[PDB]
Amino acid sequence: YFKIYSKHTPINLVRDLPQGFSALEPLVDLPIGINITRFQTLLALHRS
Amino acid sequence: ASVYAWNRKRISNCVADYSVLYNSASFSTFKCYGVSPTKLNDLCFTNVYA
Amino acid sequence: SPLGKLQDVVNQNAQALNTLVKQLSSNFGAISSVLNDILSRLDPPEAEV
Image (cartoon, rainbow over all chains, first blue to last red; front, side, top):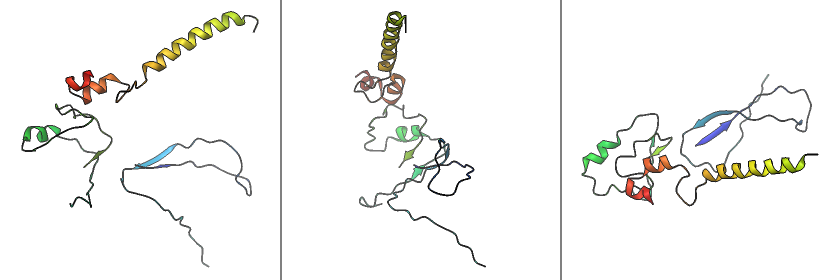
């Protein structure tokens, strides 16, 4: 089972991971039954 | 499938008829580990992997 | 903490009862700590063990 837990929060601070406590409520559990050993983050871009 | 490439199917979100397998009896070996071989495998299961 | 002796006595009793309840839900070398699942996941002969 591949479990993803999510939480959304407002933030007003610039950098370096501001402190605070927040439990992460579960979001989804994908019954995929596969092997994951590597992961690449995906980032969009802007063009004008 | 061949032994080395064991094929895995996930049995999800369906009711099961475990008793057809048991009463078929054509299965040479129907040995059950951890779960009863006396028709008590009819329990709620999160995951059935074949 | 003026009545610490009586508090210690009741705390020891409560800890003993809590330990007994916790030990109730211990596996004790079996497959599971619950007996109904043993009855439902084993035939009567194997389950007895």
